[PDB]
Image: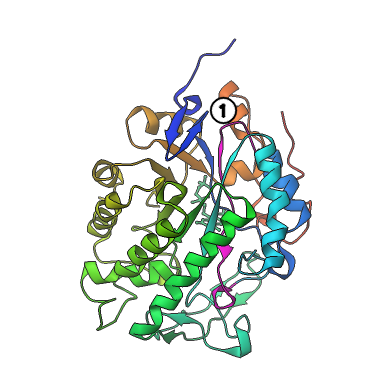
Amino acid sequence: QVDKIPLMSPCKMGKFELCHRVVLAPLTRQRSYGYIPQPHAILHYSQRSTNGGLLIGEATVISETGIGYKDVPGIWTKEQVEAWKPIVDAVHAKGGIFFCQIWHVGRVSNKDFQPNGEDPISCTDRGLTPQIMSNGIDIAHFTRPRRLTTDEIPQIVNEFRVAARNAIEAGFDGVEIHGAHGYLIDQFMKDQVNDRSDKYGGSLENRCRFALEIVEAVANEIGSDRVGIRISPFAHYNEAGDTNPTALGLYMVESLNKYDLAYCHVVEPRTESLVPMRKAYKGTFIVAGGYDREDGNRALIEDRADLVAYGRLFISNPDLPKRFELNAPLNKYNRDTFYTSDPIVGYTDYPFL
Ligand SMILES: Cc1cc2nc3c(=O)[nH]c(=O)nc-3n(C[C@H](O)[C@H](O)[C@H](O)COP(=O)(O)O)c2cc1C
């Protein structure tokens, strides 16, 4: 038959027994009209579910103030919680383990997305400069955010708490805290953004307090063994760079050891390495960013991660695990339909072997 490979090796993560190490990375596909999950997602996540395979759903918005893009799903209303259920059940029907990624864009937004035209919230009052959207035809503008006050922050921390609870109500096996790519949590961590003079700014310790308070609220709420967190210390997305990525990364992983989480998901830098973080972190380490079958196997073998998440390739190959397991050809992915809004085209029309 076929020789076993590292990527197909079983794994015990948190309270779960995974059958392989190919993880579906969190992917924003903007096909959730009205911020409500849709029927087509049922088929999407179902095509990608395998027994004991881990799936991390697209970034899900925690509150009205956390919206920065059209058609991204939310999880703060009963209507949204009910819409997720059939999707969750379809993943479970094939034996997959599903984590809901909870998110808040912070300053990466515009007043037109905000309730009452309010300004976006962030750790700073500095806004982003315009960016070109995915289609290379439209320019995205951002409103300057308002700098949250010290005693207002705990309420925001609470929003992640409720979201986490709601995901559990929807049936998710757990939640991944979105602490990467320049969004609210990352905005607080990165020194090029956090210009605060209170206990949530300045030192590396204060800048991580927000994220850590969030990890604490969520773990207490749903149990730490049902909680993961994603970070990208080295990423510069949305003008969120840090002058010492390595220490920032080491600080976070070391600080996360006391929480007994289900896992730490770190994004590879696009020198800088995740090795140190992997070494300092005592739990399950998930890595992502530019992997293929070869690099995946090598990362597992060289002890660089316990799980490897795939994004783009999982978009175009519904059966990525199977293809790696047979070292079969892979469908090419079309970035033109990554963020387009059709219910089928570029979302579920990618073929199986
Ligand atoms: C279309 C698209 C949407 C994404 N959406 C998210 C998201 O919602 N949350 C997140 O944390 N990362 C998101 N990412 C980043 C990916 O999860 C992952 O880190 C990235 O795909 C790196 O791996 P790859 O080389 O296998 O594509 C997205 C990437 C792409 C291409």
**Residue holding disc 1:** 324
**Looking at the image, is 196 positioned above or below residue 302?**
below
Residue sitting nearer the eye, 353 or 106: 106
**332 falls in the magenta region:** no
Image position, residue 254 (x, y; %):
24, 52
Residue drawn at point x = 30 percent, y = 66 percent:
208
Q: Residue at x 51, y 25 (%)?
A: 8
Q: Please identify the residue farthest to the top as the structure is shown.
A: 1
Residue type at numbered disc 1: Phe
Is residue 60 shown above or below 27? below
From the viewer's side, name the closer residue of 287 and 227: 227
Residue 173 placement, left or right of 339: left
Give the left or right position of residue 338, taking residue 11 as reference.
right
What's drawn in magenta, residue-wise? 49-68
Vertical arrangement, residue 164 with respect to residue 114, above or below: above
Q: Position of residue 130 (x, y in %)?
A: 52, 78
Mark 1 residue element: helix
Q: Quadrant of residue 247?
A: bottom left
